[PDB]
Image 1 (cartoon, each protein chain N blue to C red):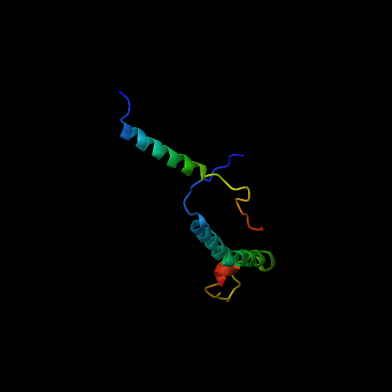
Image 2: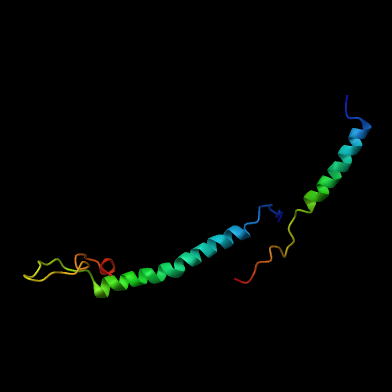
Length: 70
Length: 37
């Protein structure tokens, strides 16, 4: 009993902006995180090895992560 | 001394309007009408 109306400013637009920001961040954040996990698990990182004699590497063969090499 | 009769009349009318406004701030039993979540 005795419930009073609480006058507050319109909180609809601020919540709408926060929901839109979260949705549009996550829309590419979730696939990128999933793809990074799948790159790390299945492709994996490179292993340091000495250069074979007479062989010159490409300029992208000096990096460890697959994404950095790409 | 106390209020003038005009001050008394204005205070009475303002108090009546204030009490009506404060009564109108109460909530109906059906409010708030929550949407089906």
